[PDB]
Length: 50
Length: 51
Image 1: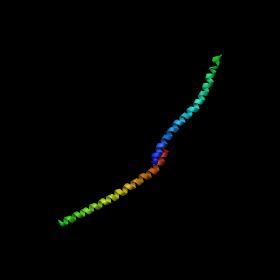
Image 2: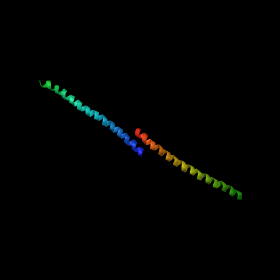
Image 3: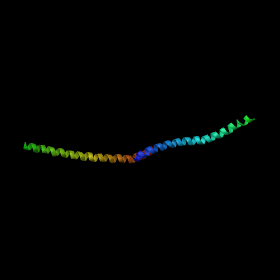
Image 4: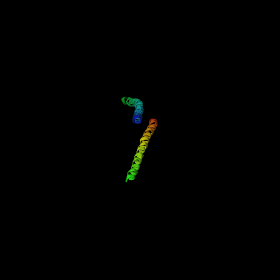
């Protein structure tokens, strides 16, 4: 039952730690990406007004 | 027929003894086996942690 414990948990912990690390990257990425969308679609919007 | 009954009775308690010792065997060995599988699990847990 203790091994049953280590197996089951250790697996889903390994698994959610995966997903969690994946979206951690994506989130840090989407901030950088929205910060580039920023200057891009605001230099695009800049000479748009002129 | 009077030796017959005593000859068969030798057979009897002999067979009965055998069976009691057979149970000594299985009763002991099935317990050794549990106390092995359990010793394995004390390791298999550690392995399963590394897994």
